[PDB]
Image: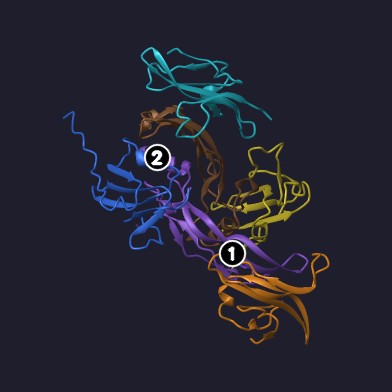
Chain colours: A blue, B yellow, C brown, D purple, E cyan, F orange
Amino acid sequence: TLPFLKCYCSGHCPDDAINNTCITNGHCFAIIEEDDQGETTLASGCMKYEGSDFQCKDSPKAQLRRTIECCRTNLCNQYLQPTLPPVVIGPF
Amino acid sequence: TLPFLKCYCSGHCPDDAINNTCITNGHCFAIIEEDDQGETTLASGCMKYEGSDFQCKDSPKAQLRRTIECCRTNLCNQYLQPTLPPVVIGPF
Amino acid sequence: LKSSCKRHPLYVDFSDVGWNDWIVAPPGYHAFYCHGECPFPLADHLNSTNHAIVQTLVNSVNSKIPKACCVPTELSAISMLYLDENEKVVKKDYQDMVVEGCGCR
Amino acid sequence: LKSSCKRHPLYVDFSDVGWNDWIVAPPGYHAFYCHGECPFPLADHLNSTNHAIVQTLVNSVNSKIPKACCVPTELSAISMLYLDENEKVVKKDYQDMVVEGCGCR
Amino acid sequence: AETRECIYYNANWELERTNQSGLERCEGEQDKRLHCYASWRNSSGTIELVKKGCWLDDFNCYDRQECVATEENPQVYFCCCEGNFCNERFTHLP
Amino acid sequence: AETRECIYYNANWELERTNQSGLERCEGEQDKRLHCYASWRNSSGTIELVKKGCWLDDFNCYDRQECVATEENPQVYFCCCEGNFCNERFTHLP
């Protein structure tokens, strides 16, 4: 229940982040997402334990296309690179 | 530091208000105010102790014309009816 | 005023969000949410802080400074029964899941 | 993103608001305020609750449900010296006056 | 205030390091109802008891003296009720 | 951590039911400076000591070894400083 896990962060780094690294009691995460204007970005950081199951599960019904993935070992997200969910075409 | 004061409330009544009455550890208040569209209303209620000195003092620079007055005895605001601050005219 | 800070309805249905595959019970629950303006003065039931009260006063003088925000100030828990990654059943009383009271902060 | 939930500057000058007649010291202070969007996902430093996390997910699915709000999650105190109604001098360490951290609630 | 007692059971009492069976006194907030629950698996005929214990105020358990699993054919059965030891016995009916 | 001691004084020690004089050990949060303060009235020549004691981290007290009231002619004088017993003595200079 104490801050023991270390993660890499990018775009979600806290202010006291040391060398693009954040500390947490929860999980590390990486997320690839497409914004309202079709741009895709990869970000990552730390996620507190409370509510991590909800966030790591995410929802298929999210309005924006995205994939978030979590892991719970030191710097496990440095090479974590999720792929976007496929776009369903049709009925055409 | 416990809820001991009883006040009359109108327009600021909590949900559990009994017969337009609220309980507090702070002060009772009554306020007369003129909205963005020139309408004036009288309201009243309970104000928690923390921050009551700031709220009861108010600010002369408030953008809307208003006068709030506080008192600290049971139902002391039932007949409390403040008057609006005068409108300064000129230089004409 | 209908527009002031208060609790609003919100039922979270696990089947709709798609969490019914890992959550066994309940099928969903009333979470509610807080929304509404925090104008001057802040009444007792809005459980504000000295800071939110001061910010409310500043906003009253200078609109460039935003008003305090309506958020949960008292939350309650609900029991959930779910399956962990190992398909193992877990019962947990999740804290801070339901809005009981809203205030300005 | 420049638009995300974070602390912003705010100096409260007692002379400007008009409280210098009753507050002797300090002349004013940095109160700061919180503002910014709370988009998905909510990082650790945003100190969110289970409820705000769930609301953030619901908003992601249904925009009619508002996002969590950016508010102070850690506040600090300052000492003030003032005159009560009886023109008597009082020293008090006012709690929750300064925003130290912002989060989504 | 209102009190409550339920039948306690934990199939995975090993790793969790708890008793396998017993009783539990529920603890609830002001004016909030208290319930009991049971959950099990149905390995085609044979029933595997998974867990039993206290459950917090839940609309789906209100005014139910008996514990009944209503879900047609779930992977994990569940029922809750409002009554002391009301989870001592349970049934399944879609 | 950082510690602090100041000269304590209370002109209204009666109603407040406290000592009229003494010392005070300040208590501050992590990495937050600690100060001392003094406040008095100047009844045309004669000085009425009002209060002295600890004061929390305040930009206006930073790096001040002496307690100096800078306000031209206030109704109530005040000065704060950063140093043990730094409020033992004070002065007034606009």
Picture quadrant of residue F57: bottom right
Q: Residues within 10 Å of mark 1 (few under 14, many from 20)?
A: some
- Residue drawn 32% across the image and 35% down it: A61
The residue nearer to you, when weighing B35 against C55, is: C55
Q: Residues within 10 Å of mark 2 (few under 14, many from 20)?
A: some
Distance between mark 1 and mark 2 Cα atoms: 49 Å
F25 to B72, vertically: above or below:
below
Tell us which disc is closer to us: 1 or 2: 2
Q: Is residue A36 left or right of residue C58?
A: left
Q: Amino acid at mark 2?
A: Asp
Residue C59 on image: x %, y %: 53, 59
Give the residue at mark 1: B61
Give the residue at mark 2: A53
The residue nearer to you, when weighing E92 against A33, is: E92
Q: Is residue E58 left or right of residue A11?
A: right
F42 to E82, vertically: above or below:
below
Q: Amino acid at mark 1?
A: Lys
